[PDB]
Length: 354
Image (cartoon, rainbow, N blue to C red; front, side, top):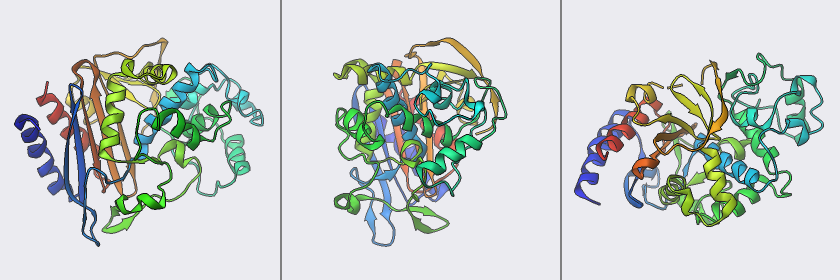
């Protein structure tokens, strides 16, 4: 990589790894359509396996970006509309608090206080129904944003219903495969286990536990290479050949709501570029916030800092790109460490490259 890129990356990441005691980490910088990869430490401390460009990391919430794009693609195909009421896709949701809650609200965490986590006792399809039927909103829809897996996760499951495909088959077929993300998985197959890094929490090796709506909200695993390719696809969607996928990517970066200096897309979150670092950096763990509707939603704005933070019990990831500068970055680590530290590192790096 150009010495410049090499230096800013190493001088920023090296101290990060040491301060946060991160076991392993991979970073990709995408500059003008070219990726440069970097790796440090261990994917598996016990068996001394190093992190490589083929190491699979749990993306955690960064998976919501794939979900937002797949949903965006379903919209482009004419299969669903964000203005459709949720009950159109789950008519069994007859409890009246659901009247007025649209797929847009589910996708952008504005349904009225859907919880951060689906409860652990929710197993079966009927258990999920019961959870949503019994949930009591704190707010009318479209008034406040409360980050929630139970919200976009539900969006993801309904989004793929007209297609006939399961969420995983839709994702592989309409998103992963077309984008040639061949080492990106919702379920890691036995053949790829040798590359599946262990996450580390309190010194113990851990992998994400199965859970209701996990695939839709936080269950994707991927390599720094596929993730860099994911970033390039989002940086330049107009270069994607699949018509609906190209529109889907654009739809996921549309600004639907505003809170403070942040705009909510489908999965992706955005701020106007240039951004104040303390605006995105300090902008840390998930609170209840009033939202102003953007009527109609603003189409993807090239001068934006588009990003998504993500974590599982043992992994910490972050993705950010500036379309206008054809610049992006991916940081994958097998330790959930403070969000502000990820954003600060990403900012030092990207700001240095323009």
